[PDB]
Each structure stands twice: as structure tokens, then as C-alpha cells.
Amino acid sequence: AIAPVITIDGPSGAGKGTLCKAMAEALQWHLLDSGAIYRVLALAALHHHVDVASEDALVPLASHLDVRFVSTNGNLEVILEGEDVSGEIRTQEVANAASQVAAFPRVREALLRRQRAFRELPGLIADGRDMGTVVFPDAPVKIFLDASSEERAHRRMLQLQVKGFSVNFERLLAEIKLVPAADALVLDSTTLSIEQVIEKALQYARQKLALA
């Protein structure tokens, strides 16, 4: 604390990205995508020639990571050391190095400290899986976003089509077929439209942080 943090946790394909981008743009606050964080670290290592298997070399790199997330019209730019690398981060190769980097206990602890460092004024929207339970347990507004398998399977299908792969809906529904904080507002992405979820999330934030 001091600066307010709104945390958004939930499973893959629930629409957290969309929500987090809409809220950061509406409020004009800082943005943190914890899912992208390990991929950015793996890319910096590749870029600097830091050995992906060396926990000792990766810790200082993680603790000093120069990244920022900017959302414009729903488009996320991932700026690493000043250059946009949003495209680079979506590769399988970077996803694979990210898994190697994440295996080490000291690297995960260094990234835990690095992510808490994003909490600045006027505030922060943070999205991930353990944002409200582990990274920012004291957050004033905590939202857990749930969605049906079909909703999640559809979101994955569009995500992959983007990289070029169009895959059978039934196949993905099979492929897809994380504890909310005690103090989280639970919102269901399938009972409400995504536009309705964003309105409902912004109203709850307002009641807790502003209004009157």
C-alpha cells in the first residue's frame, strides 16, 4: 500500500485481459499482466545472452526488469527496455524459455518483488491467477472472473486463429475440460455480457474507491 490496486484473477479464457484493458483505459491507471511477465523475462534473457539454466544469472535480471504494459483502444503494447515486443512474446520459443525460467525458486521470488513494484499512483490494475491472494493480499478491490467452458473454449479458438491456427471447437472444448480470495467480488462472464461485466466491475470499484 498507499496506492490502490484492483486485482483480477480467474481461469484462462475468462476475459480477464479484456476487462483489465478496459479498466486501465477507463481509469487511466497503470497496468500489470502477470501472465506476460515470465515471457518478458525469458525474452530479456535471450536478448542479453543470459543463460536460461542459470538461477544465479537470472535473479538480478528479474529484479531489474524494465517492462511496462500499455493498452490503447484494447491493444496491449509490451515495452521491454523501450521497444514494443508484443509480437515476440507470443512465440512458442519464448513460451518454452519462460517455462525453464519459471522452474527456479529464487527467480519466482525475484519476480514476486518486481511485480509488487508496479503499485504506484494513481493506481494499478493487475491481472493473473494469484493476484489477490499472493501478490497483493491487501488490495482494496478484488474481482474473481469465472466463465463457462464454452465461453472459455471460444476465447481460446479466437486466440489461436490469430497466430494462424484454426482449430475445431469441439477439440478445444475437450482440451479445456486458482482459489478466489475470501474478500473477492465473484463475477460470471457467461451470465453477463463482457460489456456488462466491465460496467459491473467499474461500479464496484467506484463504490469502494470514489463516489459521493
Image: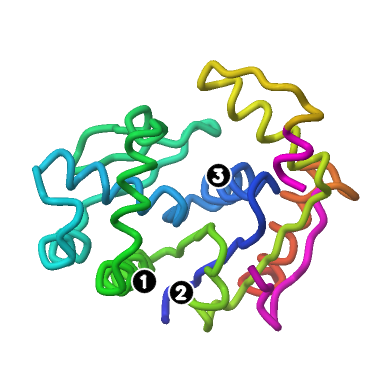
Q: Which residue is disc 1 drawn over?
A: 116
Q: Amino acid at mark 2?
A: Val
Residue sitting nearer the eye, 157 or 188: 157
Assess disc 2: are there few (<14), some (14-19) or many (≥20) residues with their C-alpha within 10 Å of its C-alpha. some
Using the rendered view, name the quadrant where residue 184 is placed: bottom right
Q: Amino acid at mark 1?
A: Arg
**Residue 107 in the image: above or below residue 70:** below
Q: Amino acid at mark 3?
A: Lys
Q: Where residue 185 sits in the image (x, y, percent)?
A: 75, 70
| Left or right: 92 as drawn, with respect to 20 | left
Q: Which residues are magenta?
A: 172-189
Q: Quadrant of the C terminus?
A: bottom right
- Marks 2 and 3 in Cβ contact (< 8 Å): no
Say which label, 2 or 3, has the lower sequence index.
Answer: 3
Q: Where residue 150 sits in the image (x, y, percent)?
A: 83, 39
Q: Which residue is disc 3 drawn over?
A: 21
Residue sitting nearer the eye, 64 or 96: 96
Say which label, 2 or 1, has the lower sequence index.
Answer: 1
Q: Does dot 2 land on a helix, a strand or a loop?
A: helix
3D distance between C-alphas at marks 2 and 3: 19 Å
**Closer to viewer: mark 3 or mark 1:** 1
Assess disc 1: are there few (<14), some (14-19) or many (≥20) residues with their C-alpha within 10 Å of its C-alpha. some
Residue sitting nearer the eye, 174 or 81: 174
Q: Which residue is disc 2 drawn over?
A: 135
At a point 13% along the width and 65% down the height, the residue shown is: 60
Q: So how many labels did they put on this image?
A: 3
